[PDB]
Image (cartoon, rainbow over all chains, first blue to last red; front, side, top):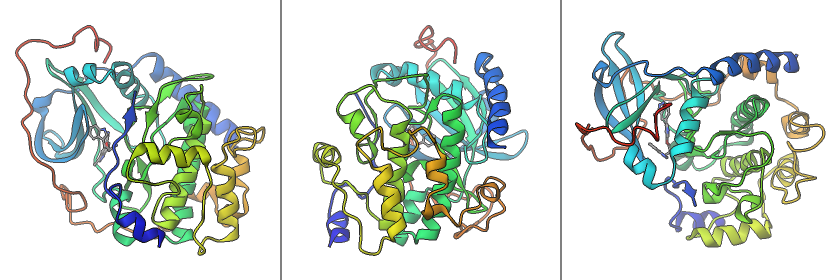
Length: 20
Length: 337
Ligand SMILES: Cc1n[nH]c2ccc(-c3cncc(OC[C@@H](N)Cc4c[nH]c5ccccc45)c3)cc12
């Protein structure tokens, strides 16, 4: 399931901002 | 009238924009309690103000780290904009000051915690729950954009839940007053509009795309475009094929198709009819915009209140000393702060 794929991913924690 | 409300809001903002408050407190006026978050050039700490006994969230930025990360102008933007704005869903900057080593922004403390935390824990929000939070963002962007401000980092991590269950927007580090186009690559991978990724000039429409991402994430429990690495996330956004959970209502999918629209002539918020395209959409048919602004609407979720000073709705972070050098660092770079 898509939920399962998300939960198994490395981006379920707080996400850092990016910039150049 | 929205128009006349916004007109007077602009007069209020302009006065503070053109004559920014400066040096309105000192570090030794606050007791430091606990770190509530950490970023690349700074952290946020719970503090108590001795004279009032009020609790605040104090953002501490290391000037030398700001310079290394090329965030000087962005930091000047953040403080200058925050001291000038006033809206029910924006967290208030109470004081600002600097010392030899650091810049300080003291904000109202929001003990209920981040939407991020509650969202991940609970899993997903029901459509009415999501709609209630989205409404507040729609009115917030309507306010900010009217002042020529772009916000540029909408995400659950930046949205705090107050004691009445309403949203407070935090972190103005990428917020900018700009008429016309701008070019900086900034934001958070999952939330970036294709224009940003493709390195075009862009405008306030990148905030309305970000709203599409937020609504999807609240209602689904995961974002529309995810992968393990940012480069893979960017590939997905630029294709822009979105798949909606089967549980998404017809109206929700149609709102999101119009927010998550690669084509700027068709993206809602950007068009001739402005925010009203969003405000008058079927998904928002039940929303009383006045009552939301007025905070008369009953919130779907009220945070557990364990008192003043309580940090239980926040995660724990490693504590680290607030070091102040005996020499002034970066005096010229931050002169106007
Ligand atoms: C807990 C709290 N109560 N009131 C406020 C106001 C403002 C913040 C706040 C301000 N600025 C940045 C914030 O960051 C949340 C994330 N975007 C992580 C982050 C990114 N850059 C920094 C810089 C310094 C600390 C945290 C972060 C929250 C927190 C609180």
